[PDB]
Image (cartoon, coloured by chain):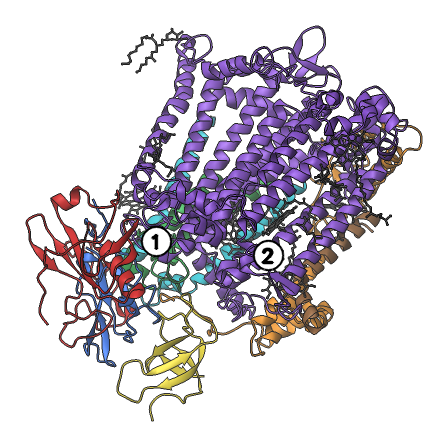
Chain colours: A cyan, B yellow, C green, D purple, E brown, F red, G orange, H blue
Amino acid sequence: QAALYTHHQYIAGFIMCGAFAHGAIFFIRDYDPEQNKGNVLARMLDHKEALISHLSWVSLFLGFHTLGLYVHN
Amino acid sequence: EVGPKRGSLVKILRPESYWFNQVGKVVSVDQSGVRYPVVVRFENQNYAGVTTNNYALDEVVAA
Amino acid sequence: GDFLVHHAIALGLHTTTLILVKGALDARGSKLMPDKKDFGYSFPCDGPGRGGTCDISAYDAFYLAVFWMLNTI
Amino acid sequence: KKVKIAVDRNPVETSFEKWAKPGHFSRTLSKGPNTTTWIWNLHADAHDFDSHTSDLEEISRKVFSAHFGQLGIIFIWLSGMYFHGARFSNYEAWLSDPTHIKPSAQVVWPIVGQEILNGDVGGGFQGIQITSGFFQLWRASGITSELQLYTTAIGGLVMAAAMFFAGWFHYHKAAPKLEWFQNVESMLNHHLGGLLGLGSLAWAGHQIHVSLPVNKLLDAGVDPKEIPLPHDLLLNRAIMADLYPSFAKGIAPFFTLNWSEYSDFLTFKGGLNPVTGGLWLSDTAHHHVAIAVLFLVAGHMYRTNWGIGHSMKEILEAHRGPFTGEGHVGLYEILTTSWHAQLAINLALFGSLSIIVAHHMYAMPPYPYLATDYGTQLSLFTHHTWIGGFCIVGAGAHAAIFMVRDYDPTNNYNNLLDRVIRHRDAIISHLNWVCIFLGFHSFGLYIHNDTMSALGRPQDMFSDTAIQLQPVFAQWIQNTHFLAPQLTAPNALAATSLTWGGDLVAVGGKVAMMPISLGTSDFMVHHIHAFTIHVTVLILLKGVLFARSSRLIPDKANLGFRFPCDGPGRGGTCQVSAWDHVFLGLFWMYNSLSIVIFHFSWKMQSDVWGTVTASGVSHITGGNFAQSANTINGWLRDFLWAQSSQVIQSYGSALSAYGLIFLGAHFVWAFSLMFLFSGRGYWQELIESIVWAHNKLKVAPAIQPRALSITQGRAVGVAHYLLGGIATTWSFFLARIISVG
Amino acid sequence: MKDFTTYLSTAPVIATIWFTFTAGLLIEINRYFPDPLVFSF
Amino acid sequence: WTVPTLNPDTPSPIFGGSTGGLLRKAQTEEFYVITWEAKKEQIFEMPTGGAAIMRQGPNLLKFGKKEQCLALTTQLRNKFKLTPCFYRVFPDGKVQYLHPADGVYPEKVNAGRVGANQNMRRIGQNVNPIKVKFSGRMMSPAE
Amino acid sequence: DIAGLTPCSESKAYAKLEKKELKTLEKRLKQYEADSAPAVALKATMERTKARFANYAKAGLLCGNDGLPHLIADPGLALKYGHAGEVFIPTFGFLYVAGYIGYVGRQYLIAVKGEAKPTDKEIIIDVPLATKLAWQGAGWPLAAVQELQRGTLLEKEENITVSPR
Amino acid sequence: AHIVKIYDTCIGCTQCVRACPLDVLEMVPWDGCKASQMASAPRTEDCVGCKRCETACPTDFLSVRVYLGSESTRSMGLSY
Ligand code: CLA
Ligand code: CLA
Ligand code: CLA
Ligand code: CLA
Ligand code: CLA
Ligand code: CLA
Ligand SMILES: CC1=C(/C=C/C(C)=C/C=C/C(C)=C/C=C/C=C(C)/C=C/C=C(C)/C=C/C2=C(C)CCCC2(C)C)C(C)(C)CCC1
Ligand SMILES: CC1=C(C/C=C(\C)CCC[C@H](C)CCC[C@H](C)CCCC(C)C)C(=O)c2ccccc2C1=O
Ligand code: SF4
């Protein structure tokens, strides 16, 4: 049980990192901004700073408070 | 004549520029028919440490 | 304990996808390197100019996210 | 005359107007911040006095006054230690019973439940068990009171005020000219004869008149309140004559050369005091007298203002051979014109000296009741070893800084420095080869033993049983020093240390010092030490010799000492700087000294330290260094995992702070890896995506947020790495050895 | 002493003073109201 | 101005030897020769590590890398105000004049050198990599 | 009775932990005399311990099988069963102070943006201005709401962006 | 070899050519429809890829761009 869980979860983590890796490779190699004029995919890059700053806030909050509660305890 | 005045505040519409959508003060506009005649000095420097850059008449807008 | 470790898991997921999303969305360019799409997915750097551009590419964001993924899992 | 006092009068106005202008010292920082890189550069360039100006006079004045500041701070620190021993201590209780009472000189306030750290150290006292050895040092000096410590603290504060006044004076009021600093002959004469000669003579006098009688009465069971005060021993010669009869004869035997009369308090006993486990203070006094004479004659060697003496320039320019060309020609100018060269040499020898101090203070415990305070002993060794390693890496750094900045090829033609730079390829190639050979034949031995033990083949290991790699040279030296009082040091009564051989000295049932047996594990770990040292030397010497130029980058001196790279070209030139060679030599010095102090801790806890319950010595770990230190799994299991049971189970104890700092140092160490494994280009883009959110809410600062420079990223990473690792080892060591020792 | 008070208004000095103040306030609050796990007063 | 032919009878600075000099690359593919005229005997720094004395008059120096030759060039021009020119030498004996290709140094103009690799667009006007995809070799949109 | 959690006043593991801590402290106390400085310290520590346990059991805290107080983060369960002072009340207590800090720093930035060198007013703090704003930032929620409703809290699309927007 | 392109934002400051440690760039007259000079890259087979040129370019964004291409003995800066 332990081996199967750890196995499939590490496999999943690697696969999920590769998902975004190839999403980036798409944005560089395959993405045409003219043929995606105004669709959800371009709308992503349009407000990408908002996405990244909010992921930053969630990461920062969770780290601050999880580490702080663990250190308090 | 062409370009904003030599003390006007001007906003940059070049996307690859560090000061895109940022307001800078015009230093000089070359009346010669040259590419990028507008010299804009900014109060915050770019990643290279430069505070001024040359911009075209397309890439600058008033205020 | 499950609360605290689930929030650590959330921090890990959110930071891993922060690194990955930020490498996927800043993949076609940034303020530091607006022409990054012209340099490809993987490339070493853009030199020590403009303050320093070590680990600038999307490949480097993936490489930084694999550490945080391994820590999450 | 040539050697004279030379100063400028009121060179610098004492004014606060430059306090209010951060970055005044630089022309690139006086323009004010626009980015945060300015905030970091203001601190990186604060003490780079040779980058503020370029004339050596102001540099030297700044250096002198900053040294005065450092001395004032050291005096504040010493006065604080003496004051905490006078006010927040169990020292007077510890004198009466030093074998049972734990030295403590720090009390914690009861605020957030942290009064649990105020542990039951003994003497009706609650505080933090200190590991500094200050109690033993004070007992060796013959303090016996908190009033004397208090007045030493007041004197230290007075001397700190004096040092700060002297810095202000020698910068702002009467600052020495350059020709005054370049009197290296007179400086050496005074620092040998006066700083070390008169200093050792004065300490010898204190020991003759204060330490020896006070400690002879303390060792005779006399309560410290019944002991005469030092001034009663100074005034009344009858008391001293009652303790040491030679004092009845006065100072006449000294002037009549009847020095053997003083064999009562000037001895050559060697070994250890069996009552305290420390060195005989009579031997120590004789030592200080001898080296005082030695340094006082040494300080009459160099020519200053009269015809007698040496010109160091002549000595140098005369020392040359058929292999070395012009020889030491041009080194006097180097070392009288470049501060960084002097700093390189001085840091090198000061760090080697700190490590030598570490090795000599555990084997010959100089203080009473120091050898059986296993925590004090371990902490002192570890501390001075670390300080030495850091100083040595700094020596490499500043040799590289000299090579980049102050090196001139005109003054160095075919001299030793030119000829070293001219065959640097051979130097570094052979150093690389010996590093690889040592790495193999040291660590691959551990790997071979791990593989054999895992394969079920202990008869194939490099052990004291199967394939003995006996350190026969070290064993011979041990036996030779043990038998020295018999043949080669006949006026010594015993050997310098009990580590050479013989019997143990037990103080309070615990072993003060006992013979250290060297075997296959000691062979292997000493060659590990040699390996790590050689690799650290490789990195730092490669940074020095390739600081100006390389086959990769021929104009590296123009890029500077501290630059990130030249670019991603030539395949990539990251960390070609000499600064980056220091940055890597720091990691390797850490990896070296960690094993050094681990070897010390385990060897001491296994083969030296322990209790004498019956007739027979029970060591702390049980003598498992011999059979378990052959493998990496033994160091992991029998040292790291086993001896961690005191630092991880310390919660709810007075040692709980050590577990907390263990965990926090682990955290800081791992946090260093965010700066070491990463690069600036990710963080600048993340910072600009965050600056977007700040601009949206109109909280974008005017000082533009930048990511840390590449060099600063590396510096932060290595600083956090060193801090985390060293504090982890600190907590582990102290929590372990306060419990088991 | 305009320049001295300009120095005291610098970021590190002001940060030191402000955080000494905040830490002392928290420390005194925790001395006079010890062990505040929950808001019950 | 015309291409100067490398005079092989040029003396060399006084140098006691190093280990940073030529390697088998000089014997196999190419090495580099830098020549300059000095007004007086001066000690300069070798890019290979070490101090050499350039002779009064013409001086010839061998190097195994162009960056070494141009480092020495910038040193001689900035610390001594000389005017060196260096060549590429092959084991065949073929000498290729390199550095002041036009005769003047490239930081100044000579009115007659032709511009190369000049894109007449802005750097933000490059096409997307999806437009140069499958161009044979792997390419950047800057071409 | 929220998630199988018993009150700390009724839990036996809670009392066991109290007596365990007190036994530790008194086993330390046995080593010293009647009124020593260590004895005074340990008696004060024992009093603080007893007071802490009494004040946690008095505050209606819920305890687990380990006898340790567990906090209720959920509003609705905290407000139904009187556990709002655990996480719910200190939530707004914190948010007030955090918005205080942020609003004060924001107002300082906006006020120093007007000066000729706004950067030197950030490394060298304008202390009178900072203290004025720190005092008048006590009404940060109302001022922030009114700055939100005027459309003057946010900047429009004058913020800078990378080339692919 | 490495690709060194120069774009029409060049102001003829000559600093890219001053900073190139390989003599890859030079200054040519009136190819850019600009003031007197424009930068050129006629010797990109000697370019190592240091990007010292575009560290010295003051325009925003860079008027000189180095795209690291295929490596050779000269591009990898080998004395061997
Ligand atoms: C369906 C799965 C899938 C597919 C088809 C691809 C296909 C591709 N990927 Mg993607 N990728 C995937 C999953 C996948 N990947 C996952 C899961 C990850 C995250 C881990 C990535 C992360 C990733 C990155 C970051 C990049 C690619 C790239 C590529 C391209 C070329 C890779 C290459 O040259 O291989 C060569 C691969 C190797 C030589 C393997 C390297 C060695 C690895 C680390 C394993 C070593 C194991 C070792 C031997 C174990 C020793 C143990 C022993 C000692 C006991 C190709 C289009 C590249 C690309 O398109 O460039 C533009 C690129 O940059 N991929
Ligand atoms: C223990 C190691 C460690 C820690 C603590 C972190 C912490 C963090 N990483 Mg990760 N990281 C690590 C290792 C680590 N990293 C490694 C090995 C790598 C591979 C290179 C990375 C790669 C990486 C990337 C690529 C990214 C992060 C991000 C983050 C941040 C996530 C937000 C967060 O949790 O905020 C909580 C903050 C912490 C837990 C650290 C602060 C600790 C306390 C709370 C601060 C105060 C302590 C004390 C008062 C200071 C005293 C100073 C002085 C007085 C002595 C945070 C700073 C992301 C980021 O920065 O975006 C937000 C991101 O994109 N990291
Ligand atoms: C009040 C007395 C006073 C005054 C007004 C000045 C004024 C001046 N000095 Mg002088 N100086 C003084 C005392 C004074 N000095 C003393 C006592 C010394 C001996 C150390 C010196 C040594 C000295 C040198 C060597 C130099 C100056 C310089 C200067 C100029 C600017 C210095 C600056 O920016 O200060 C602001 C700086 C500070 C506040 C830093 C103080 C750091 C102290 C000494 C060490 C504290 C370390 C601390 C304990 C570390 C804690 C770490 C933390 C994590 C706990 C200015 C003319 C410099 C100059 O260029 O003059 C033209 C210069 O090079 N001074
Ligand atoms: C017998 C004479 C003598 C003595 C004792 C010293 C002692 C010292 N010198 Mg040296 N020095 C001397 C002569 C002397 N010097 C001469 C003649 C010159 C000119 C060539 C110099 C030039 C010189 C430089 C350039 C530097 C020193 C430094 C030092 C200090 C090194 C740190 C140390 O070991 O801490 C040991 C600390 C102590 C032993 C504490 C006691 C300190 C006493 C009070 C000062 C010594 C007496 C003083 C030299 C005479 C003037 C007394 C004063 C009241 C007028 C040390 C205190 C370095 C330093 O740190 O500067 C501050 C340094 O940078 N000295
Ligand atoms: C620096 C180190 C040092 C110092 C300070 C002393 C000091 C002393 N030793 Mg020790 N001693 C030392 C090293 C030292 N010793 C060493 C290394 C050895 C081993 C050889 C000894 C061995 C030794 C023995 C065996 C004896 C001493 C004794 C003495 C005392 C007698 C001094 C004496 O007769 O000399 C003469 C010294 C002087 C004449 C100098 C005095 C000058 C004064 C201070 C002049 C000031 C006048 C002023 C200008 C005007 C007045 C001021 C004001 C009122 C107006 C004296 C306390 C003897 C004793 O009685 O001990 C208890 C004794 O029997 N010593
Ligand atoms: C006698 C000792 C000595 C002296 C006088 C100097 C003096 C100097 N060094 Mg050298 N150095 C030394 C020892 C010494 N160093 C050692 C031991 C090392 C190895 C670590 C180095 C490594 C070194 C490098 C690599 C460099 C220098 C540089 C410099 C110059 C400027 C340093 C500066 O501005 O920092 C000002 C002070 C700081 C920035 C503070 C640093 C704080 C450290 C990183 C944190 C540690 C603090 C504490 C112990 C940890 C706990 C803190 C707690 C709050 C958590 C100056 C000439 C630099 C130079 O010349 O540039 C061209 C340079 O690049 N040194
Ligand atoms: C610890 C400490 C302290 C204190 C210290 C002390 C107290 C010291 C002292 C010191 C001293 C107290 C010193 C003294 C010295 C002396 C001397 C050094 C002497 C000498 C002599 C001689 C050298 C002689 C010679 C001669 C003779 C022999 C005879 C005749 C002739 C003649 C004169 C020539 C303090 C507070 C600071 C704080 C810190 C720490
Ligand atoms: C994390 C990280 C960063 C980001 C780290 C940031 C920029 C530094 C953060 C330092 C502090 C937190 C900022 C100081 C702000 C104020 C001085 C603090 C005063 C107010 C406090 C109370 C908040 C890099 O810039 C970097 C660069 C190169 C290699 C590796 C890394 C790297 O690993
Ligand atoms: S330091 Fe930065 S620019 Fe230099 S080689 Fe490394 S990644 Fe590239």
Q: What amino acid does circle 2 point to?
A: Lys
Q: Which sits in the foreground, A35 or D276?
A: D276
Determine the CA span between mark 2 and mark 1. 31 Å
- Residue depicted at 71% across the width and 60% down the height: E17
Secondary element type, mark 2: loop
Instruction: Give above or below for C40 relative to G24.
Output: below
In the picture, which quadrant includes the N terminus of chain D? bottom right
* Residue at mark 2: D4
- Residue depicted at 48% across the width and 36% down the height: D589
Q: What amino acid does circle 1 point to?
A: Pro
x, y percent for residue G41: 86, 37
Left or right relative to G35: residue H13: left
Mark toward the viewer: 2 or 1? 2
Instruction: Give above or below for G95 relative to D596.
Output: below
Counting labels gives 2
First of labels 2, 1 by sequence position? 2
Left or right relative to D503: residue F95: left
In the picture, which quadrant includes the C terminus of chain D? top right
* Residue at mark 1: D409
Residue D293: image quadrant is top right
Letter of the chain that mark 1 sits on in the rendering: D
- Residue depicted at 30% across the width and 69% down the height: H15
Residue D641 visible in rendering = no
